[PDB]
Structures are given as structure tokens and as C-alpha cells.
Length: 257
Length: 257
Ligand SMILES: NC(=O)c1[nH]nc([C@@H]2O[C@H](COP(=O)(O)O)[C@@H](O)[C@H]2O)c1O
Ligand SMILES: NC(=O)c1[nH]nc([C@@H]2O[C@H](COP(=O)(O)O)[C@@H](O)[C@H]2O)c1O
Image 1 (cartoon, protein in one colour):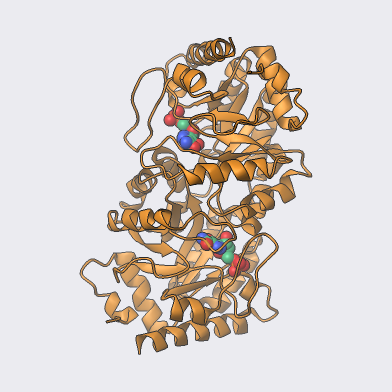
Image 2: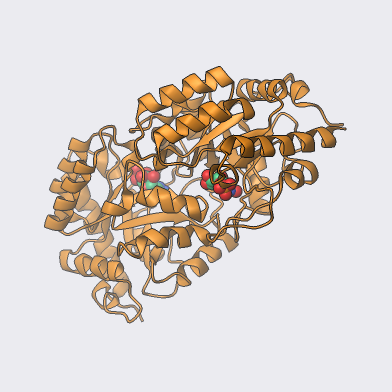
């Protein structure tokens, strides 16, 4: 039988980052992750402040910010703390373990210093997770494994998906869930976050495909929707975020009973 | 029957970036790509200058440079032009097409402005290539697809590898070859570049596994070796680069007949 987000936050094997997330999802009645796909720091921060109460998570691509500085990420943290959401840097680490460790901790971005969550592809084998965890464990961070992809021609299917689930369930000290289209693990300790979400049917011109919040949270059993253009391209981004929040939240409630 | 690098440079379907690379490989008698895995710009540039005559390519991870600026990449270009080698940013693009387009052109790194070559994982489907090509084609660049990985537990095997080959062979206006452990395409227009290379047997503590230049270039039929620590950790990096260059070049000559 299905547990609420609040009860899942208490599970024996829950990761502290997962528990923090699940608690604020329950408190705020939001399972929406804003994909803050903008190139300006000022727009990122204005969106984070205005939409903060509507979201459980803000997903970044800091490598697309034209004016990235670590001070921008300090300001983002201030907002994340005020409004209570996690920061997820969507870096898709996908190299050998020795390399990703440095990409996570170092360089200009110093991702591990400000990101609560990051994600990784499983294609390199479990060394990708072991390399990240060398940095992420001492910094009390979590990681999401990409088990499925929303794009046309995705190879993250079948045995590849199963390998991602196995990898997560064997690195549960650091891996807190999946990026996936559907529930892929039967262990309620793991989060499922689903991108490729819009209210209307369609896609983009570069292989992105959309499903609705009701479809992915209800029928497909995911936990959280990740929404970029469905919100960002709207004239009123706050009203769009509220539309997506209500859709995902109701879908969850109805699945729960 | 096997063609020399110089003859491959003249093939009807050759990409201009591949032809430039093959020409300089033949001229300089090198099929060594230095993996310049350092965190200091000064060390990067000192290696590029000293080892430039020994290498056909210098592979970067600019997201590990602690002091990246675009002026560092301008100085790297000066050296690449002087010594005649290509710059390969090992970014492993691995997102939906719409996202990778921005990660390639924009942000702080502006990768497309200075990298002759980049690479991509094929897991998202061919939209990853189509997104990159919408920046890379107008900038006259090339891309390599990751068809296999050197690390323990790699999922880039079987039908996944075949899908990478199909994707390359269908985007030949932009994709110039592979990162792989072995020959994966039987079309000589495509380059094969192989990482996980050191003279001695072994590996690292995060899943990297090594094979020798003779094994990779001779028996496995690859074109170019990519070497990081085997060179970078040596006391005399120039002597190490020469050892690797001679090994890979003579393996090529012997396979050619
Ligand atoms: N793993 C996946 O299946 C996957 N699909 N999309 C994304 C990311 O999620 C966002 C989707 O954006 P929008 O289409 O505008 O809603 C975008 O940042 C993209 O990079 C992702 O990680
Ligand atoms: N199979 C693959 O695709 C693959 N294996 N290694 C690398 C990259 O090549 C380099 C290997 O480094 P070193 O072990 O020191 O010789 C390093 O930068 C790593 O990120 C890579 O792209």
C-alpha cells in the first residue's frame, strides 16, 4: 500500500536529503520542480524568488548561465532557504569516476558547494557513482540516476533501466532516486523525478516529447514533475507554476487515495 | 585493404575536420591525443607548448580548470596552430537536443568558439546530435560519439554500440568518429579514438581500466590513443609523450603492413 510523502520521509532507509525534500513537499503541497532554463542570473533569481513558494525544487543548468558567479549561487541558496526548496544542478555527470569527482567539486562552478542534488548517467558503470560520492558524501549531498529519458530514440530502456535501478539500490548512502518517466523502483525510499512534462500534448523540434502531469504522476507513478518551457515561456510564470503544481499535487493525492 | 591516414584524409565522404586531423597525423607521425588533465591554466599551456610537436590532439576538461578564462583558450589556440594539433573538449554532452545546443554555444565556457571537436553520449537519441549540429555545423566543427567506454561496468556495449555507429553514420556532416575501445565502424572516413590507455597493465581505484597502445591500435584497430595519467603523472611529461607516440605510431605502421 502507498505511503504519503510525509510517511516516506520517515522510512528507515531514507537519505537525509530525500527526507528533507519529502517533508517540504508535504508541508507546501508541491511536487513541482521548476527547470529554470534561462541564461541570465537576474532572471534565474527573480524566478526563484517569485516561484519559490510553489516549488519543491529548482533545477539549474549553470553551464548555460552567461553571467554565472559563485555569488549568484549564494543568492540562490538564500532563496532556497527562505522559500524551502532544494537546488538540483542538472549536470548529467557521465565520465569515469576519477574525472567526475573533479567536475563535481572543482573548476569554476564548484557544483558540490551549492547543489543539494546532482544527477548522473549510468553508462560508465558504477564508478561514476563512486567518484561522485567521494565528494558528495562528506558534503552531505544526494544524487539522482538517469534511468530513462524523455527524448525520441532514448537508449535508456530495458536492461539499461534495470542497471540504473540496481546501481541506485547498491549506492543508497548517496543515491536518493531517479530521473525517469515512470516509477522504476519498488522501494519507496527512492524518489522518482520526471521531465518531459507539459499540460498539452506535443514535443519540441529537437526530440523532446511531453506527457501530462496527470499521466506521469497518476498512471506512471512518479513523484515529482520537472517543467521548463511549460512555465518559462509563459507570460505569467507564477500562474503557470501554480497550474503545474495543482496538476501534479492532485494527481498524487488521487493515486494515494 | 587498409588505407594510410594520408589516404583516408582524401576519402570522398571525409569531414573537413577529420581530413585536417588525418593530414597532420601523417605529417607529424603522431596518433597520440594528450588528455591534459590538470587544474591550472599555466600547467595546461606549458604542457601544450612542450608536447605540441608530439601530439595530434589535446583533449581538455575545461570544467576542471580552476582558473578558466576565454583568454586561456585563446592562448591554447595559438599553441594548437603553431604546433599543429586539434583541440577536443571532452564535455560528453548527454542531454536533450534543446539543452545541449545551449551548453555547447553559451554559458561561461563558449565551448564551440574554441573547440575543434567535442563528444556526446548517444543515450538521449539522435536529438543530442541534432542539437549540437545546430551550433557546430555553422561553426565548421566536428563531433565524436561515445560508442564504448573503458570503465568497469560500462553499459555502452552490444546494441548500444551499434546504435552509436548508426547515429554517426546518419549524421556524417558533423560526426567524424567515435570514442571507443576498438574499431566499431567499417567505414574508413570515421576516426576511432581510444582512452583507457597505458603502457603497463592496470587500472585506477574508480573503475578505469587500461590497455596498451599496441593492443588498442594493433589488435583492436583503433586510430588514436588518448592518454592522461600515463603522461601527466610522469616526472618528464615530454619523454612520456614520446614513448606513447612511438608506441601508437609503430602499432599503426605494423597494422598497415
Ligand atoms: N532525463 C530526461 O529524460 C530529461 N528530459 N529533459 C530533461 C531536462 O529537463 C528540462 C526539460 O525542459 P522542458 O522540455 O523545457 O520542460 C531541460 O532542462 C532538460 O535538459 C531531462 O533531464
Ligand atoms: N571510455 C571513455 O569514453 C573514456 N575513458 N576515459 C576517458 C577520459 O579520458 C581520460 C583518461 O584519463 P587516464 O585514465 O588518466 O588516461 C580522462 O580525461 C577521462 O575522462 C573517456 O572519455
